[PDB]
Amino acid sequence: IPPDLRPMVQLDGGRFATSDLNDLYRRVINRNNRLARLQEILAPEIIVRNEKRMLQEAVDALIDNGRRGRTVVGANNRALKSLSDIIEGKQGRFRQNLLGKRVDYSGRSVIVVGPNLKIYQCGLP
Amino acid sequence: HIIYRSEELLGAASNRYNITVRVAKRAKENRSEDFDSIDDPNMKPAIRAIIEMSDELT
Amino acid sequence: MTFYNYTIDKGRLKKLIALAYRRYGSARCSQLADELKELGFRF
């Protein structure tokens, strides 16, 4: 994904506000560089078989977290946001950013009853 | 009397979604023709397109 | 014009609003409901 769709900003206290896509992308490359390291030094086959199984679980948790195996977590004990979990839910990209948007030139207030007026006329402060 | 002029325009037209495009396409001509220093605050170009279209309807 | 010589309820008011739509349209029907609520708020 492009990096602006996984933004990394810094807060006022100095901490960084990372996304869950950066933690799932890093699990793929860390297990892919280990597989290229084990295949170069002629590792035992019980370690290469276990490394390819974790590479299969890293991509599947990146695409749909919690579909086949167990749901991976991060620092907080909530579920990580995968690539598929941002489009299917009620808080996904379809039902919260495409079918319904927050508009400009808008506002709200409480309403009171206006008598001595007409229809097609409203009181505006 | 603007709401009485709009009900006469929507009637005898057979398509209420087509005669409102001709009002919106005439208000842009009245806005470009009113580019001089004289600007009437009471007669908007969107309101003047409804009065001029109802006078030619008869 | 007709003369309504009976006591007016809510259901008899909706027949008057529906009769003004069939004969006069929407502009005169909204003016009738605008004047009927000045009469109700006063009395």
Image (cartoon, grey):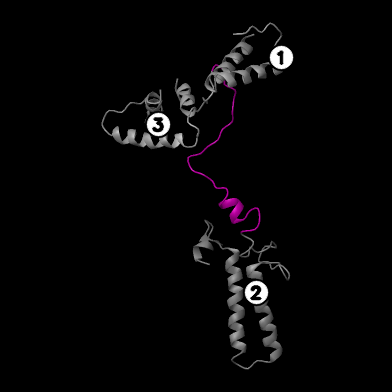
**Label 2: how many Cα within 10 Å (few below 14, some 14–19, many 20+):** many
Q: Main secondary structure of the magenta part?
A: loop
On residue A121, the disc is none
Nearer to us of marks 3 and 2 is 3
* Label 1 to label 2: alpha-carbon separation: 72 Å
Residue A97 shown in magenta: yes
Nearer to us of marks 1 and 2 is 1
Residue C7 visible from this viewpoint: yes
- Kind of residue sitting beneath label 2: Ala
Which quadrant holds the C terminus of chain B? top left
Furthest residue to the left? Answer: B36
Which quadrant holds the N terminus of chain B? top left
Image quarter for residue A13?
A: bottom right
Q: From the top left corner, tell me how far across and down residue B4 is, in percent.
A: 47, 21
- Kind of residue sitting beneath label 1: Asp
Residue with the mark numbered 3: B46
Q: From the top left corner, tell me how far across and down residue C13 is, in percent.
A: 67, 16
Say if B32 sits above or below C43 in the image. Answer: below
Q: Which residues are magenta?
A: A87-116
Residue with the mark numbered 2: A58
